[PDB]
Image 1: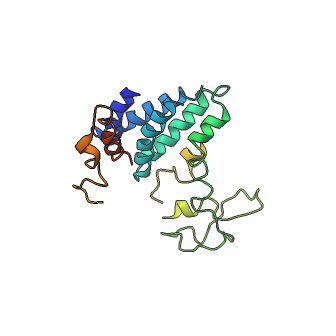
Image 2: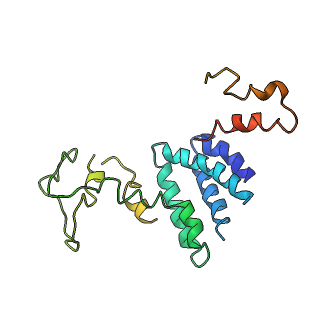
Image 3: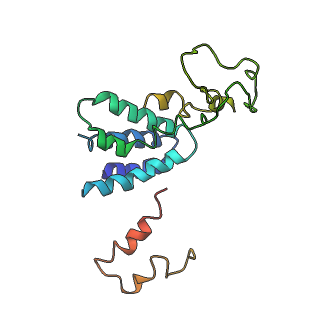
Length: 154
Length: 35
């Protein structure tokens, strides 16, 4: 945890890299806590991870991917309560990133709307259509942590 | 409060900070780097 405290510098940004290595180390040290006194050093050195995640870029997506790899690697262990404390605010960021609407046949603006005229690709196996993966994809410019692939993996 | 001041900052109790209050004025100051 002092190495990741050193990675706190890495997480802060030593160079063009080391922020990535920070989150790989952070989630790896986190999964060792998944199977108190060390719960406080966990959350303080987690808030920097949330900070770099709160910073705009794909460094949030990497935090998502890493939590996905942690659930994938240790499945029988890692009880539900500990990981729920870790991610329930990262899971629930997908189905409300944009999909809270009612009639998805409209376009809104759907910025750069090439598929305002042909939306709603072929699945049809549902009973509601709120935005259905369209509106976050509209504006898109995302690294698909945004109700998309790395977030769906978690 | 102010960025160089004392009362809301670590320098309020730094006039009588001790070896135990060393990493206490440095605790609230140490909180100002997360996020």
